[PDB]
Amino acid sequence: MQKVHVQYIDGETDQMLRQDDLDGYTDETIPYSTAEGIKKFEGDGYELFKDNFPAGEKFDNDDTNDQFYTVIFKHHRENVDPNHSSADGTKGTKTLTETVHYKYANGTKAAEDQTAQVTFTRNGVLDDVTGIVAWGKWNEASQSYKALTSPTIAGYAPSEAVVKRSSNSDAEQGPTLTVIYTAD
Ligand SMILES: [Ca+2]
Picture 1: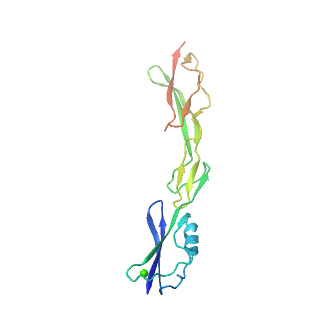
Picture 2: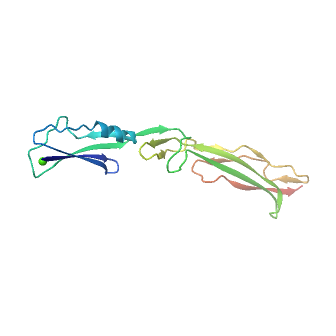
């Protein structure tokens, strides 16, 4: 009897996913199609790259050696929006917070902090096999915080009347700064 092995391969990770064995008679047409196996793996996110099983291939007349044929896949990808989830828990969004403290010259507190927030977004490409999104560059190079008006405190003037700042998309946290109140 002759033997044939059809090997289903992830060609991105060079990993064998399954092997199907068949036996037959010399010169018999190999009674196999890669169609079901291709359908199955495409259902798990793969995309056919190269099917090396030849149409109408016969079993050989070589007892010593088996026949091997690979069916090679890549990972199917699709572009996704910033709101898309990812199996590795990474996100297409981030929100940074600006914090402004209000103090007198000795560091004692003059008023309660005010805060503001900015949000950045990034598109990505989802790998259908892994469920993981490869996120691209942040779409906005920077974002500006809403203007924060320092409170009016009788008898004092703030070092900065209205605080306007921005964050760059590479920042991991927004700015934290102090407005100082000086006596009139
Ligand atoms: Ca053989």
